[PDB]
Image (cartoon, helix red, strand yellow):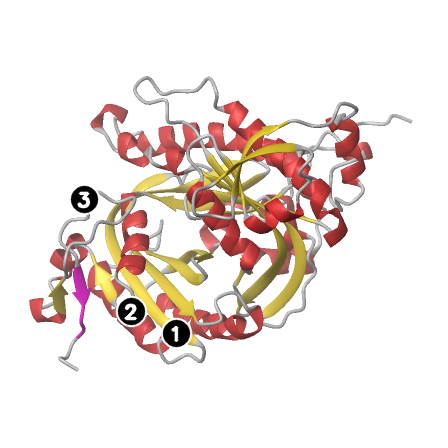
């Protein structure tokens, strides 16, 4: 009998799993919300703000109304190269959030030392991709890398139709702190990463006023062979593609239909992505330069990285947020930690989600969220930034690992406003002027220089309907 080759496997379940890390795809978690798990690992934070900063040049008339298509193409070309490096070195891309790619090597505590070596090599090879790189004006197609190691907590929250996950804890805080110290082309190690690493592998430089360190070179001992070392490390990598499947970038490329698993996984993916996955919408429909309102919600906790107390509080906040956004087809695009606060990136006006009077609705939704979350047990401070304008939306990443992402000056502005004007609902001039709500519902704010934004325009506090 003939032996014809297996079909290229591109079942819906495989297409869904492209949008999710192995942490979720193979997690088999309890249905309970919140769900908390605890493990150890090495985190890599790749700052791709240098790539995402391209949204401005692609809004130019030079791109002839194909700005979004051109942007997604060049962003994915460069980001795919980073993704392939992380996956080949055995990492799990957790999230494309906060103009960064966050990757995880989950390993038993005893193996952290050897895995840091693998992750440092990976980090240097990432930098090596962009060594002879430019874009005919600026050479700043480069990245910054922060690494951390240690205890990691995972939170899964949501309801019966939607699920979100977050990683929590000191190593999560550390990796963001480490990447923030990095200059372009740097690999910075968190204090605990430096303490846990194989110091015989690396030459470091002190970081002024910091216990974090900078990797100058990976200079291994004489009898060292990275390939044999890597092979030894794969013993501890549960999902590294191997044997029959060593030619695939992810084990998840081999996932077979399984309705109970697909029911679980689809809850992490928004419905317009699932429409595309089901071949019920054109594959290019979600790549667009679209006017939206960003409502960026930051929740601060006293117990800044203790999953047992912050997990219920986030789930409580989520249940209210989701109820508020449902009314106006608002979506939660991303949730992630920033300086130990939990941030919800909410978007009004996604494709096919429109709704007229988007601005006044966005403000009223923000105030509703503000008032409710301020009374949630263990939430110390709520801050909300509201900014409106043209943003890039689209699926960013590699074919085998990508996520729907919103990028733009107005996303960064709403994020910076919630940090620089804590404890209040703030909005930009577009939102203030467009809302047509009476002027005394707002307070014109002092101008703050916010790192990443120049120049914000007049900013306002949404005070609300009454003097209160
Ligand atoms: Cl996360």
Choose between 349 and 449: the one closer to the eye. Answer: 449
Numbered range of the magenta stretch? 460-464
> Which residue is depicted at the point 61% across and 35% down?
120
From the viewer's perspective, tell me whether residue 275 is left or right of residue 12. Answer: left
Q: CA distance from mark 2 to mark 3?
A: 22 Å
Residue 380 circle label? 1
Choose between 222 and 45: the one closer to the eye. Answer: 222
> Which residue is depicted at the point 53% across and 41% down?
213
Query: Quadrant of the rendered structure where residue 58 is?
Result: top left
Which type of secondary structure does the marked residue at label 3 adopt? loop
Say whether residue 462 is magenta.
yes
Residue 455 circle label? 3
Q: Earlier in the sequence, mark 2 or mark 3?
A: 2
Q: Earlier in the sequence, mark 1 or mark 3?
A: 1
Q: Residue furthest right?
A: 1
Give the overall secondary structure of the magenta segment.
strand
């Amino acid at each position: 009998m003939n032996t014809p080759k297996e079909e290229f496997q591109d079942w819906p379940i495989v297409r869904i799993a492209a949008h999710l890390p192995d942490l979720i795809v193979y997690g088999h978690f309890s249905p309970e919300r919140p769900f908390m798990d605890y493990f150890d690992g090495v985190l890599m934070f790749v700052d791709i703000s240098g790539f995402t900063a391209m949204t401005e040049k692609f809004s130019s008339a030079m791109y002839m109304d194909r700005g979004a298509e051109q942007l997604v193409e060049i962003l994915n070309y460069h980001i795919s190269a980073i993704v392939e490096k992380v996956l080949i070195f055995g990492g799990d891309i957790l999230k494309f959030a906060g103009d960064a790619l966050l990757a995880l090597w989950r390993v038993e505590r005893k193996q952290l030392k050897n895995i840091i070596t693998v992750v440092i090599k990976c980090s240097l090879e990432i930098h090596g991709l962009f060594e002879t790189q430019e874009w005919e004006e600026g050479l700043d197609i480069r990245v910054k890398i922060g690494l951390a190691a240690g205890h990691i907590s995972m939170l899964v929250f949501g309801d019966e139709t939607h699920s979100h996950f977050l990683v929590i804890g000191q190593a999560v805080d550390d990796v963001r702190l480490a990447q923030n110290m990095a200059q372009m082309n740097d690999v910075i190690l968190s204090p605990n990463c430096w303490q846990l690493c194989d110091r015989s592998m690396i030459e470091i430089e002190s970081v002024p006023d910091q216990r974090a360190v900078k990797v100058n070179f990976l200079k291994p001992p004489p009898n060292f062979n990275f390939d044999e070392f890597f092979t030894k490390c794969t013993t501890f990598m549960h999902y590294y593609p191997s044997g029959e499947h060593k030619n695939l970038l992810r084990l998840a490329c081999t996932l077979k239909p399984d309705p109970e698993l697909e029911m679980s996984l689809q809850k992490y993916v928004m419905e317009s992505i699932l429409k595309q996955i089901d071949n019920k919408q054109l594959q290019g429909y979600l790549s667009e330069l679209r006017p939206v309102t960003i409502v960026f919600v930051n929740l601060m906790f006293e117990d800044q990285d203790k999953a047992e107390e912050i997990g219920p509080a986030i789930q409580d906040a989520y249940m209210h947020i989701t109820s508020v956004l449902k009314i106006f087809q608002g979506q939660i695009n991303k949730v992630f930690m920033f300086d130990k606060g939990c941030s919800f990136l909410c978007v009004f006006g996604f494709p096919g989600e429109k709704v007229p009077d988007e601005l006044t609705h966005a403000l009223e939704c923000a105030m509703d969220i503000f008032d409710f979350c301020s009374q949630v047990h263990k939430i110390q401070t709520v801050s909300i930034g509201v900014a409106s304008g043209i943003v890039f939306c689209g699926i960013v990443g590699h074919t085998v690992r990508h996520e729907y992402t919103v990028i733009g000056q107005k996303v960064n502005l709403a994020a910076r406003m919630m940090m620089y004007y804590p404890g209040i609902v703030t909005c930009d001039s577009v939102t203030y002027n467009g809302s047509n709500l009476p002027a005394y519902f707002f307070k014109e704010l002092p101008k703050k220089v916010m790192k990443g934004v120049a120049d914000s325009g007049p900013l306002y506090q949404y005070w609300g309907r009454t003097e209160k």
